Image (spheres, coloured by chain):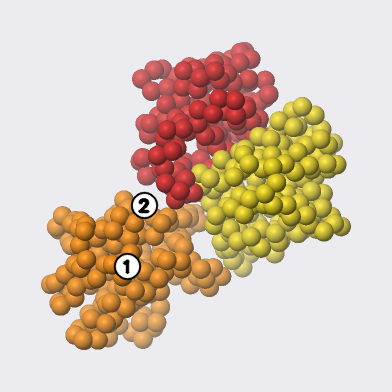
Chain colours: A red, B yellow, C orange
């Protein structure tokens, strides 16, 4: 069926994910979290917009007002992509590669359909989990664990 | 936003594709059928996230409906496809939709919508957008202006309420027991 | 600038139309056919006028060509249509054109173009733009940064020069007798 990354289901899922990341950041304040609309300007020149992003406090603080106002010129420490029916797995997997190649330190891919999650880190093979309720995202995001059932 | 005039109303298919081809940009269809485009920079993105977070937190503890983030576009009665920074839809209204309707731009007016003024947006255009929401059936429209540190609440049949330098804002009874905290949005 | 992919090259016609409907912005066409939208006005607009005025003043004295402010867009061989903050076109070239060409987006590369960095522009993106000007025939590209209070000069086949702490920059031989004064642009 006709699906849009900017449609209801995708929006409902990305908010559920972003909500958790924000809940965690509210208590720890180690960085700044952005929603699915945010565009970031990556080192390779392109603009990319994940479903959620976390940028380390130190990286964010180094930015000027103008840089924070526009598409931030940096690779977020962590990026999250929630697969929507309109996207084929290998495509996002390919995108996770692009993120890492640009300096993202943690890429999390959630597939609500397959009901799995894939964790991408540089200099390490991709990790795929299925059947787990929560997934620890330490050490990149200290004390944060992503609860999966809410994303389904 | 920037207006792109077409001698043809942009289509839902074209909106999806434009979103795809332009990460970081929000595409919308006006009531007259024109294209509206606005970028979502870092500041906008952190504020809308924080606003959606508060709405979601409230909803998780209450369970009255469904919350959507800022990338979601809704299809209203007059044909416009608008994308607020946050929206709340009651369960009943959401469930009534077909799997296809939920997956595409939901054909309904969220009970409550939120818009956060970005630096590149003129205040009056955004206040006007609030009127479009209301005339299409939205029961609560909230406009946050982080630059003036003010918030304006719009309700059908009521004078818009503009509050300045306040810390909290009760959005009862449309959103039972929810109070939006403003400093986190500055 | 805001880069927009309409999934097809934007036509010259649409560029004008878009400028009309969105007056406070500059509209250009990239070599790939995408839309480049940039903010107009503010102190940046003021700097543009100051520069064009220094140029017009010099040209009045020498009479070698035509001066343009930030409002003109030029059509280059690669199909891009760019609008610098100011430009100089040699008299002969200008007249060799058709009245229509002179009235729209002149189809020629100015001998010299000037770009003044505005607050939302990345220095590296402006430098790449200078690269586009030169590969399309511009003989002298000048980039003014009022924030870092520096100037960069680009000539084909030569390394880019950056000057700081200077009050004036001579632009011979391309603009004989012309020295750009910087403080007025800060």
The quadrant in which the C terminus of chain A is found is top right
Give how far across and how far down residue A124 sits, in percent: 39, 17
Q: Nearer the viewer, mark 2 or mark 1?
A: 1
Identify residue for label 1.
C185
Q: Is residue B13 above or below residue C77?
A: above
Q: Give the quarter of the figure containing the N terminus of chain A.
A: top right
Q: Position of residue C160 (x, y in %)?
A: 19, 56
Residue at the spot of label 2: C122
Label 2 neighbour load within 10 Å: few <14, some 14-19, many 20+: some
Say left or right for B20 vs B10.
left
> For the view shown, which residue lies furthest in the front direction?
B165
Displayed quadrant of residue C56: bottom left
Q: Is residue A141 above or below residue B114?
A: above
First along the sequence among labels 2 and 1: 2
Taking the image as shown, residue A112 lies to the left or right of residue A141, namely right
Q: Chain of mark 2?
A: C
SS at badge 1: helix
Pick the residue in front: C23 or C12: C23
């Amino acid at each position: 069926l006709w699906v849009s990354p900017t449609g209801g289901e995708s929006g409902r899922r990305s908010l559920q994910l972003a909500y958790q990341l924000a809940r965690w950041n509210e208590e720890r304040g180690l960085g700044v979290v952005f929603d699915s609309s945010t565009g970031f300007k990556f080192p390779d020149g392109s603009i990319l917009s994940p479903d959620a992003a976390f940028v380390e406090r130190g990286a964010w603080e180094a930015l000027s007002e103008a840089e924070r106002e526009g598409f931030p010129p940096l690779a977020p420490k962590a990026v999250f992509e929630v697969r929507s029916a309109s996207q084929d797995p290998e495509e996002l997997r390919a995108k996770m590669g692009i993120y890492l190649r640009n300096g993202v330190l943690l890429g999390v891919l959630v597939d609500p359909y397959a009901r799995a999650v894939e964790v991408f880190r540089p200099g390490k093979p991709p990790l795929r989990l299925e059947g787990v309720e929560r997934v620890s995202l330490d050490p990149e995001l200290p004390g944060f664990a992503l609860s999966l059932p809410p994303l389904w």
